[PDB]
Image: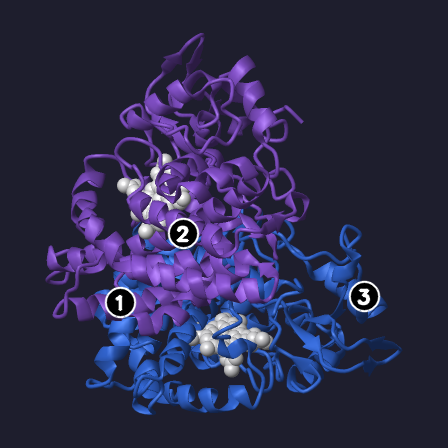
Chain colours: A purple, B blue
Amino acid sequence: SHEFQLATAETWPNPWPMYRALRDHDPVHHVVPPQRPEYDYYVLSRHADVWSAARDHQTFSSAQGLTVNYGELEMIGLHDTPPMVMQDPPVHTEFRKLVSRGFTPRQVETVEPTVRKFVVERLEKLRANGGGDIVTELFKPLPSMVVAHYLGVPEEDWTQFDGWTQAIVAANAVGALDAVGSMMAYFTGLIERRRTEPADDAISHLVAAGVGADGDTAGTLSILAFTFTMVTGGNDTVTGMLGGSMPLLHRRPDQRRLLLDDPEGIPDAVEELLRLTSPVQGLARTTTRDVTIGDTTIPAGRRVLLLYGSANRDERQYGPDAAELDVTRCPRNILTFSHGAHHCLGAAAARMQCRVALTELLARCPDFEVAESRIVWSGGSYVRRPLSVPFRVT
Amino acid sequence: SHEFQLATAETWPNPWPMYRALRDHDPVHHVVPPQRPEYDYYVLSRHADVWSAARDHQTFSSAQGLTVNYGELEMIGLHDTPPMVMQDPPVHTEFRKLVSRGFTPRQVETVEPTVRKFVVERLEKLRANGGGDIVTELFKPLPSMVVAHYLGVPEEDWTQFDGWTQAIVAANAVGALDAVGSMMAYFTGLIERRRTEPADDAISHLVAAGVGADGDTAGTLSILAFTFTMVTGGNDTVTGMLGGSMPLLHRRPDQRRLLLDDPEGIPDAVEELLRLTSPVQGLARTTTRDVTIGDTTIPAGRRVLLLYGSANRDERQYGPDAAELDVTRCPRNILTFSHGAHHCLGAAAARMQCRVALTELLARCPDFEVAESRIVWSGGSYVRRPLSVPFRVT
Ligand code: HEM
Ligand code: HEM
């Protein structure tokens, strides 16, 4: 189909033709669901429009939620302590300033050796076995460890924390009461501990800055909400980047050759893989005013889907070859991590995971096979990530 | 309709004819959903069968959930720390023994004066106004205060705790992430405090008995799960009892007269109101073996709905007048609180709330009007409770 529809597990394999039809024939596309026309919304598919809209938080607000479902906030129960990703400036600004103290080059650097050691252990296990499911074995557990690091979870607690993570990621994707309860409970204790034993992580930084101090329960709640944002934001996305890169690399031995011969080209290659996988394929905003983009006026009060995945594939920005892998492309202004106020805090951490995984795949498992038709994609309309990528090595 | 269907807001007004058709023509009724026949289940509608099945936890297990939906436990996320209501003996037995220490006559007696003071304040406010919505004003907030008492929540925290309660009750009925997180967070702190400042409540008793002691995180989790059981079990049910009693009393001035002339008959009247309102109208079990009841064999591995609401209206147990209010009936072996291992821990607390509310309604607002067709019932197929009961007083 070339007709717009929110993605499902069955339609994630190849949304690209549908994106191209939108970019070419209806860049400001009005969706009116036949069964509930009251839930109409708009879709932005071009790079220029998505880039500008992401930046313009004034006009395009995050404060009513990030899906095209108008009942979202009440449906999930996120009105009273909205996560930072559903806050507009100025509310968003102070908390983002404080938490950013846990997202410096230091925090990416300190976990890199742990990432590499884990990637190596799992890839060697897969190699010895002639392959296996690289998602369950590596691409799923890896990002959970990195989120744990950023939350200052002691290494000894990583296995327990991963249990909760996986339940929440599954429930969030498209149902995790024990996990959401156990986690919010665990973090209550960790926050308390960080009052007297602060480290360099984001939770320690929030506590040290006085968030939740002197009976400010709302502050403590904001820290807890941040842990949920981290778990829901830093896991399935990374798995989508890592798993989604596999067929792209497999089908382009010329591109693998470039990186085998020049491993120093791997950071640039990571940008290209991020552009093409765009794990967050789209997120919504709500218009605060009527806004005209080209020949269409979007009314105030409607949801607008920013199709990062299409923006990243826009021939107007990247050329007629936008749909193809070119590891030397050095794409700029990618929308994989959005743009503006909410630009992904974990961008450096995601880039580091991609770099280490790609480096070790080429070094340890260079003769590998992926069957694209055997990939199983997760349900859910916003994030594109595989549940399984069968993987064979010789 | 007289054809079996799970109840909705629209069908809660009058399920009784449908129950009677089941009792008379298909007491062991096989439901095969046309759209998903793989989700077939059975319904028990007679008192004798429901009484025996509730008692026989061996044959009729709670461990797979309490609804007729086979995916229930994973859908809600309650596998890893199953609540006590979804535990079978022997697992269920120790925890129930420990927590029962917080459900003695002492705990009902200590909160009664607070209940009465609140009922009085709200009824006087309604009287002064010539009526209003007795659900929002009284029948909703009251049971939340009583659950707070049983959880050892300090009175100063009751307003905050009610906020979370209402979100969870709405989400549980048929979506409360901030509430479920804030509550599980709050209780983590309260449990910690009870380690050194124990009171006579159920949480204090669990902590004093060593549940969660010495790094036993699973124990602490069980206490947290119990708070959720309490919030989901002790609120909408009581509101259903109180609100559901209103039309029954209104339409029977002879029955009100009996209690105006003999207020000492009110405890017995409460049993009759519990029988007719049966707020938990049904809950499911799973068969562990093939079981024959009359001419029908229920296979092992299927859900069986125990229709407490029909059992309570069974002419075979209560007589041809089973459908009618008789405050002097003194019904015995009611199934309002089930029967056997899981018999409602809050039965005494529910009975006390009914008694106080009924006593004060007759004393303060005896000339009152309820329009049954104006009552709005909550969605959800298991608990029958109004969201609104318009109420007028002269
Ligand atoms: C390839 C992997 C990732 C992708 C594609 C991705 C994508 C995004 C996007 C698109 C946003 C902005 C959302 C919007 O437009 O409304 C965002 C925000 C965010 N991301 Fe990521 N993310 C990734 C990995 C991570 C990781 C690993 C972490 C944590 C270590 C993380 C933490 C966050 C946080 C905390 C925000 C909220 C920032 C704010 O609202 O100010 N992300 N991410
Ligand atoms: C009219 C009001 C109430 C009704 C109709 C009701 C009904 C029930 C029923 C039918 C069960 C057994 C569930 C099953 O068959 O699987 C139960 C269990 C339970 N109820 Fe209630 N309940 C009411 C009020 C309360 C209150 C006020 C509290 C707390 C103060 C409470 C706490 C509990 C608990 C903790 C259990 C679990 C017992 C166990 O599984 O061992 N209930 N209730």
Q: What kind of element bears circle 3?
A: strand
Q: Residue furthest front?
A: A261
Q: Which dot marks residue A232?
A: 2
Q: CA distance from mark 2 to mark 3?
A: 41 Å
Q: Is residue B117 above or below residue B267?
A: above
Q: Around disc 3, counting alpha carbons within 10 Å, would you say few (fewer than 14), some (14 to 19), or many (20 or more)?
A: some
Ligand 1 shows up in which quadrant of the image? Answer: top left
Q: Is residue B160 above or below residue A358?
A: below
Q: Is residue A177 above or below residue B33?
A: below
Q: Around disc 1, counting alpha carbons within 10 Å, would you say few (fewer than 14), some (14 to 19), or many (20 or more)?
A: many
Q: Is mark 2 within 8 Å of ligand 1?
A: no
Q: Residue furthest top?
A: A295
Q: Which dot marks residue A188?
A: 1
Residue type, mark 3 in image = His
Give residue B186's position: percent from left, percent from top: 28, 67
Q: In which image quadrant can residue B276 be found?
A: bottom right
Q: CA distance from mark 3 to mark 1?
A: 47 Å
Can you identify the residue that label 3 sits on?
Answer: B30
Task: Please state the chain letter of the residue tagged with numbered disc 1 in the rendered image.
Answer: A
Of residue A280 and residue B336, the one placed in the foreground of this image is A280
Give residue B299's position: percent from left, percent from top: 81, 75
